[PDB]
Image (spheres, coloured by chain):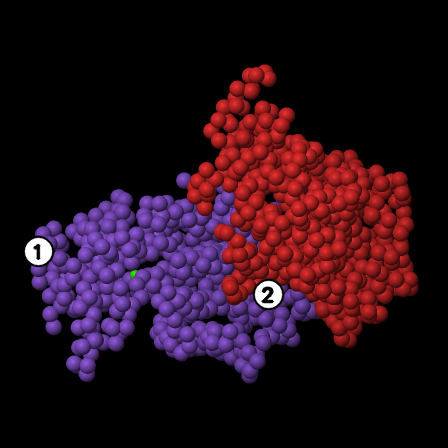
Chain colours: A red, B purple
Amino acid sequence: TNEKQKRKRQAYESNLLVFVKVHVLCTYAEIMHNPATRSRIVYFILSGINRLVSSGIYKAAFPLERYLLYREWAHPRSIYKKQPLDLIRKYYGEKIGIYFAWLGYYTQMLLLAAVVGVACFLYGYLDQDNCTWSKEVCDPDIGGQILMCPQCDRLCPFWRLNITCESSKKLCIFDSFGTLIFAVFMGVWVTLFLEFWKRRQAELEYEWDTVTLCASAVFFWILLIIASVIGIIVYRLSVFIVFSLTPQMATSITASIISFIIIMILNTIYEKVAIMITNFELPRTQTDYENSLTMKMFLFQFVNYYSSCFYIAFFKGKFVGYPGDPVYLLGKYRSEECDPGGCLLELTTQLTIIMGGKAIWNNIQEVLLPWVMNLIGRYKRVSGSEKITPRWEQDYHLQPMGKLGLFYEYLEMIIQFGFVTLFVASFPLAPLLALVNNILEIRVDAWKLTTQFRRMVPEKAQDIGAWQPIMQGIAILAVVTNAMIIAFTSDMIPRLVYYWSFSIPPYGDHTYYTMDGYINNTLSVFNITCRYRDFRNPPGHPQEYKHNIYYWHVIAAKLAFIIVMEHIIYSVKFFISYAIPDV
Amino acid sequence: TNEKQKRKRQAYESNLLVFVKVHVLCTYAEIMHNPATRSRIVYFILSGINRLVSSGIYKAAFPLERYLLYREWAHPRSIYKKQPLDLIRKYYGEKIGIYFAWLGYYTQMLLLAAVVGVACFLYGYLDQDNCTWSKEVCDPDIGGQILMCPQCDRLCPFWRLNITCESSKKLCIFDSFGTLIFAVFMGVWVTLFLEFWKRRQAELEYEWDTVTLCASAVFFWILLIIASVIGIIVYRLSVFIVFSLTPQMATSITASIISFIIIMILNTIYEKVAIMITNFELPRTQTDYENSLTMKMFLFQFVNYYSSCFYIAFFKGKFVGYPGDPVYLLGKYRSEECDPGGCLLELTTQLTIIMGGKAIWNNIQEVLLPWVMNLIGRYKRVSGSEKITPRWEQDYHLQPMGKLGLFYEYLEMIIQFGFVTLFVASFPLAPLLALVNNILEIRVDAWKLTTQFRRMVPEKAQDIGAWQPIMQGIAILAVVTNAMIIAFTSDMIPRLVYYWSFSIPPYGDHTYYTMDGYINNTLSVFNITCRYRDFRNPPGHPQEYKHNIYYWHVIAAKLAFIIVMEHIIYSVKFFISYAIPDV
Ligand SMILES: [Ca+2]
Ligand SMILES: [Ca+2]
């Protein structure tokens, strides 16, 4: 088979082991409208090998400025001046450039989102007067004797408040007053992050050149959607049994680490069932591979990373019934419940260490797997000199791309943008944590492209393309979810109601507006026949254990901010996208 | 000045009273990419006169097939076969053609919207078993003794039910069961009317060729927004004083006639203040005139026709307070209220005779003002012969366009599409009334173009253009308003609640689901200190005259269908616009 495939390979070099060099040349600059442009036009000559190297008759077809960009841009000692994006036009082109001008805007776009991120902390820390939510809940005279009900069935205490302080003394920097001033700003921010990037990418476009087979692709997927939902809870059933810093702070760190392992394990299966379902029927041509992964493989990650953070945010503390009745999981066990702090703090750590545990892993995986940095420097000293002439000889130990270019390093930032927007009600410093990360990620992704990897073919790509109907398809799901976090996951809207409708002399007993005395006034008692975090009629009502006015009031404040903070921020989506200067 | 302007006019004929003919000719077919095409290219030669004829040095520059299109398409005896749109390409082009293929689709698009329009009547009429809403309300033993409160202050009775039958026997064909089956279909219909027209117009595109000055433009406008709101009520104050078929049927006909006069009078002022505010600052070039009228002049009509139908639908029966307290109109009078039938029937006639009183006026104004039809036929007999050679001599008594082409005849249909969609919860036959109207309007607008008017310059226009961000900007406001009619204006959502939550043994006294006994169970009593149509706590409550569970429940069903029937029909906007065949 050595000579059987040899006669095929020699036929292709006619129409122009020791590695081959390449170099007529002007005659293929007209059929399509600098060394990167030199490596561009030879790939237009080379266009194909899609099936030759994948068969194995060839091994690696490959290309082969550098010095200055190790100093002002890719050095760890690179002081913050400009991020010269214009060089990445001449160095790496506009596949990689449209991601490295994405970040550098995104980094400066996360600047003002972090000063409004420091804003919920700056007067969150400098004040010392909380209304109730760190005053009553931590003075153990007004939030000490609040004897609650258990949640689980067996191995469960009776429970008591004043075990909730260390979570709910630092919850009023994620609940108290800046949270509706930055999550009203974050829905404004993503609807300004998009539309100012549209003004930016057009400016970037002006600076630069210009039913049966898909059924079982989705109907087999929903068995794997619920595989992600059952990923978090069974290893929720593990760690909370073997345990009971210490109360729930270290455990909320710990339990979301354990699922984050299984998140990265089921990540590998998603790399091996996307190919199992696309190789069967309708493989197609070159541009529907990436448009399959955009609609299946990111969508795999969207159910891996986010359909357990949709489990803490949307369907965790629902269906508490008549004897604290769960649904029984249409089986023989008991279903879970939530805690009277707002369920967010057990989301804001799962928000943290799925985000700031991916940015401390998926960059440091791209640091330690390339042999850790500064062996002796890579080739800077002859980068000015360019006379390293067995340099073609010194290759083929270096690592190539795995026929997907930015896609893996681009999905991991859309997952990050899917956490700095879709889940931001809590934790305003998720910009500042992403700020210093996008200080470093714009250095180490600059570092590995400049030094570590084989030089990519400078494929001119115009606009993000396929992830653009996701960045709209996140931002229209985010302003729902930023609303559904302050509605269904945060306890501010019940804190606005009591401040505006339950401390007025109708249904309340105070003269003017004050937030004094909130936690005993906002839950529902459950007889021995204790309070639990729901709003139902107390036992011994006309219609007991069905809802109050006050469930139905704050659900009609909840459904209102899902309506008003949609229709305002959906209209600032209409007003800013009508009234900005294009140039 | 006769010879002063004569020397200007003779200079322009150099570079080529008795009317002039026109006719080198191939040499201007290349600079831009059949008699209509003959009149096209000479206007490209003629391009300009924008300032010459408007000054007065000329009188009318003008152009000058016909026979066959009076027979199969424009005849009253034109049997329904095809509507040959392809002829309007060769006869009138694609300014007028993109409106006459708009209608012919729209007419067939209103076919299925009228069989689902007959659907709320077909089993609305063939059944004779109403649950309650025409049984209790018209058996005068269960809806006879329902003694209500007055609404106004002086010259007002105590009032009683069983005066509401003739409105509420024929209200269960606009409320009972088909209304959530066609208004769920109408939000589906407009989000299928758009997206199938997008597939149609592309098919039509394949068949055919291819801060200070605007501040006081809007801040003076809001004084005229409330001028429209005060247009309806003062002549509401007139007619209801001089009165009291006869009970309220003839009056709901009458009062909406009187405002419809003032609607057409304030229509004339809007034609004379659009020019008053655009001639002052930044007049501009030729294509921002129509984009001024799209954003001011239609917007004038959108407040003329619709900000009194937004007064019956959104802010008519709100702010009923503690002694039935209105707001007092921050003045010294008393503000109004609504009636316990759902406020829709006093909207569905204002829906009718602003729609079916514009389609019986604005077409019949274009019939009787051109001298009523068939004087003797116009020029059909020589249309085959074409030898009427003083035909240029016989013109200049005929009427021209007033420098706006389709715009007036195109605004009046967008106003119609703004009633067959934005206001459709009630009255399913608003397709069938618009069906036989769009049988006739596609004949008489075909008739006046073919016979009555001077032939328009066949200006090739590609897509509707400026009214396309209105047809999206209606359909995103319609699925709000179709929701806000069943929420804020119709009494079905309170009829689903009692059927599902107030006839169950919690808060109700019946075994299984039945709608028996609804009107005494759904209003709130008001002491002499009678029921009124609101849901407040009865006098002698813990917190009296503030709301019930049941206000807050049905407002949380109201805000839910504003949320769910948005997010479903806003996602069928995402699913049909992802999964239809383009070709
Ligand atoms: Ca990376
Ligand atoms: Ca007309």
Kindly indicate the quadrant of the structure image that contains residue B329.
Answer: bottom right
Cα separation, mark 1 vs mark 2, equals: 74 Å
**The N terminus of chain A lies in which quarter of the figure?**
top right
The answer to whether residue A550 shows anywhere in this view is no
Q: On residue B534, which mark appears?
A: 2
**Pointers 1 and 2 within a single chain:** yes
Would the CB of label 1 be found within 8 Å of ligand 2? no
Identity of the residue drawn at 51% across and 27% down = A13
Q: Is residue B355 left or right of residue B538?
A: left
In the picture provided, is B133 more to the left or to the right than A387? left
Relative to B353, say whether A304 is above or below: above
Earlier residue among tags 1 and 2:
1
Q: Amino acid under label 1?
A: Lys
B193 w.r.t. A181: above or below: above
* Badge 2: chain ID: B
Q: Nearer the viewer, residue B341 or B104?
A: B104
How crowded is the residue under tag 1: few (<14 C-alpha within 10 Å), some, or many (20+)?
Answer: few
Camera-side residue of A559 and B521: A559
Image spot of residue A396 (x, y percent): 67, 32
Q: Secondary structure at mark 1?
A: loop
Q: Which residue is label 1 attached to?
A: B387
